[PDB]
Amino acid sequence: GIDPFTMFRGVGTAIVTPFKNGELDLESYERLVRYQLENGVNALIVLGTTGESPTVNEDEREKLVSRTLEIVDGKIPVIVGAGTNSTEKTLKLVKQAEKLGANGVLVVTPYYNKPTQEGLYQHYKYISERTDLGIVVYNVPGRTGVNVLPETAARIAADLKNVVGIKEANPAAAQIDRTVSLTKQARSDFMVWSGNDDRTFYLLCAGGDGVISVVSNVAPKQMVELCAEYFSGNLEKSREVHRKLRPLMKALFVETNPIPVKAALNLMGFIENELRLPLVPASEKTVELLRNVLKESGLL
Image 1 (cartoon, rainbow, N blue to C red):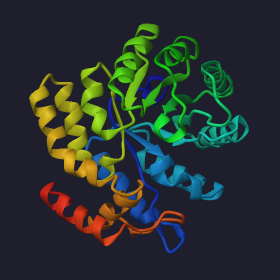
Image 2: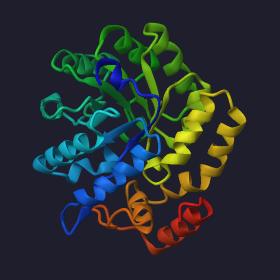
Image 3: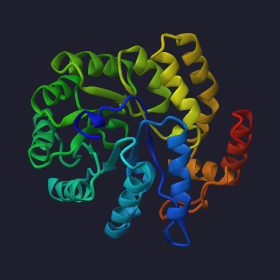
């Protein structure tokens, strides 16, 4: 229950934030958390993109994080989405998370101007010295247009002892190979987690540690088994899980996440199909697609 505790293996769920009639729906949230825990999920990432952090206010954040830690009761680490534009807003969010008893924070690259690799290093360094929390670097160039180079991540690994790992959401095989190789040469136990469900198998085969997952919101058993079968030497069985997850993995992104994942959870009876603007509930097409995909998947 701490220090190496944030070095989870396998699946960390980027959990949605259920709403009902404008307010947090903590009752539904608790049912979803138990779905995750019961199925072997090894971490929760709270208030990331999937959790609609941009539309959840300061008090709601507090109540959601506190309820999360209550249900989990130190069984698995709870990591809180905390990165924003300025190092001002970020650190405060990191402080809030720490004050509440979260185990780590997920910290996105700054985006404004033309962040250099030194810029990125200096960003994680300042946060690093000002917290005792585990810090996860979030590299997501497809969204930000900013890429943490594998050598930059390895510097971070070498120098910043409380940076535990990287959520590597650059899907490129050439980046993944080197992110894994170089960061673990700099620190044996620096964690590399896939930031893309469909790259999970590839990243594991490359020597990585699991996935920070959208798909495990609806299919935690399956995503857990993908990782577990790999770590047991059964690639054939691991591949097979990956193969069968492909339709679901594709369906959850036919609209902007978390739009489809919330529609799917609602079909499955876990939550209200309610999103905060500018996100909107999924189209009937998305819903019918999800209905069929979830039925084939045996989840409905």
